[PDB]
Each structure stands twice: as structure tokens, then as C-alpha cells.
Length: 180
Length: 180
Image (tube, rainbow over all chains, first blue to last red; front, side):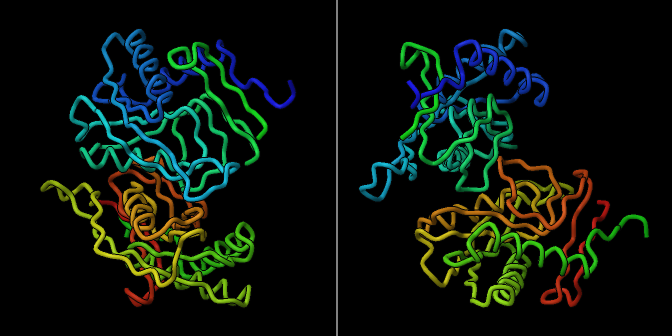
């Protein structure tokens, strides 16, 4: 059992998202004229949970969009994690120009997925600003990107992988770190 | 005289660049296989100064590239600062793929110029990472960008402008803050 450790149990996930929701409301005037955009399949589901939490706290709906991204690599190396983002498409159901957008990512690692998400946003509109909310920050950035909202920060080596499980995809809520 | 204040005199500029040069060498194995790329006219001149400082400390030359960017705005508002970057072109004289690149900016403000600089880099190659060095960070980010190396951090309001003067452009070395 010693090559996996739980870094967020289901309670901690709920608590972290609830805290992020409150931080969004405090920093962004109750989230009027602010849109959440998920990246990664699990980032999308997290953005939808966050929108529902903000609606319950504030009483007004929050719009959610999605950016569909797959990460590839240029070589045959299985150890190194996928680090070249391909934007498959995007669906943001309202105009973002002059609005605040918050990108929602499950795990902040190299920053490359975020960079492609910002590019996809500025391709469809001219938001007044883009912020970044992440469930876990595991360090090892390869770009000059930082999150505005963080569920939990953990130290990691490059030999490790962080796995997020969500009910919607995986039929359970958990975050764990694994040795590769 | 009370609508301008000097935040870096010529001594402080020299000292800040010398400190950034040492920090680059400590963090990046003496800057072998690391390229500096300036953005903004003054960011280019700063990158060339930094390269010369690293050469003097380490003894090996450092390659400098340039990205040519002009900032525009979509409206007639003179108060708000220019916030839409147009990449006019780039000249990076070596391949950047699998190399470390450091972008050099004079003043970090919204982050939008940096975002266009990263995009221009990933359009011509696949660097192993991109870092960011700035002479001054004046806050008020509009994107989730942070510098890796900072000469000086200052608090500012949106009513203020930061002016960098360099010998190469302005015939003097100074940084000041002004009330708009």
C-alpha cells in the first residue's frame, strides 16, 4: 500500500471547493459578470460543482463553459508526463468580452494546459481578466503561471503522479499521489 | 515635483540586474542551454545587459532573442493603459526546442504582453520551460502570470504609470512612478 497516499478524501474535497467558492465571491462582487470555464474532463466537473456552490451561497446562477484539451508528447518516453496541449474545441455559452473568467483545473502541474486555456479564451473574446482556480497545486511549473485559488498545495517529485477521482467520471471522490 | 517619484535610480538598476543575473546562474546551471528573449523595446535592452552580466560572471556567451510587440486598446479611453498585444514579429537566432527560455520584461503589469511572448515562443519551437524576469512588478495582473525574477516590487494604483528610462533609448537610466 506504500506507493499511493491520499491527499484529499471526500470531505476534504467538499471543504476545499466550498472554501474556493467563498473566496471567489469575496474577491469578485458575488460573481456577477463572472464565468467559470473548466479545462480537462475533471476540471469541467469541478467548475460545475463550484457554480452550484456559488448559486447556493449567493442565490444567482453562474455560467459554466468548457475547453476540451488532450495532452500529447513528442517522443516515446512513457515516464515523462504528457506536455503538449491540443485544443479540440470549446463551448462557452455566453459572450466573455469585458467579463471576468475563471479557469478551473483539477491539478496544476506544468501550467501548459492553462496556457492553452487562456489562448482559447482570447480566441473567442476579450475578457476583462482571467483568473485560475485549482483543486491541487503540485508544483513543477514549466511556464510563469500561478493559481489565484488553491484547494491544497503539495510537494511532489517528478517521479510522482497525482490522480483525481470524481463521482461523475470515476464513481468516487478522492485525490491521491502515486509513485511512478 | 510631487506627481513623480523615483523608484530605481541608476545604481539600483545596476544592482537589480546584477542580482537577477546571479539568480539566473544559481537556478539554471550557469545558463548553459538557456536563452534570454526580451519583450518591449526596453525589455530587449535589459535582456542584452543581463546577457553581458552573465558572460562576465560565467565566462560563456548567452544568446539573446527579441519579440516585437505593440499594445493597443479597443476604445477611445485615454486613461486606461493599452491592453491588447499585437506581435509584429520575432527574431530568435537559435533553435529553442528543448532549451530553457527566460522572457525579459521591464514592467510587469497586466501580464498580457507576457502572454503574447509565450505564445510567440511556442509558435517557433518547443522550449523545455519558459521563465520570466522583470525589472519592476507593479501588480494588477489580469492573467494568472507571475515573475520568477523581480528587480523590485512596488504597490501601485490603477491611476499611476511606471516609466522606465534606459541609456539606449532615453539617454538616461531611471525608473519612476507618476500620477495619471
